[PDB]
Image (spheres, rainbow, N blue to C red):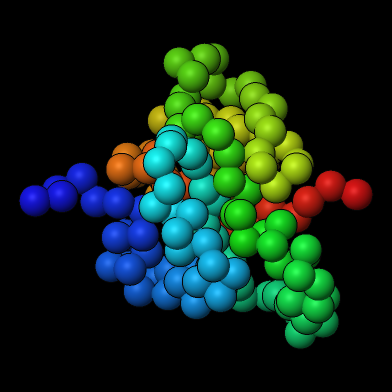
Length: 140
């Protein structure tokens, strides 16, 4: 059964997001991915980690509020949908992280303020999933 696959189920079945399970579980969000409600999350792949400076990663874990902000992975309310809107326009959306994210879908391709996503739209039991290849920094 459970052929719908859940958020945690995916992260637990996808070694690609093993790192997430580690850091996300440390913050105690493993339960947050199970909570009841439809939300969207932006999970970057290893190819996105390539570059992160030693100081950068440290400056993040250096503050509980810092890593926390990123931990939410820009968690947003309401499963992200193409909003059947015009493709090419950047739509502004607010997330729990406290910042805004610009979404733009063109040529049946999801382009968020960063480039071409690796894999998203994945329908979960607690919302949808969004896999990108770059971390989205907050606002000044």
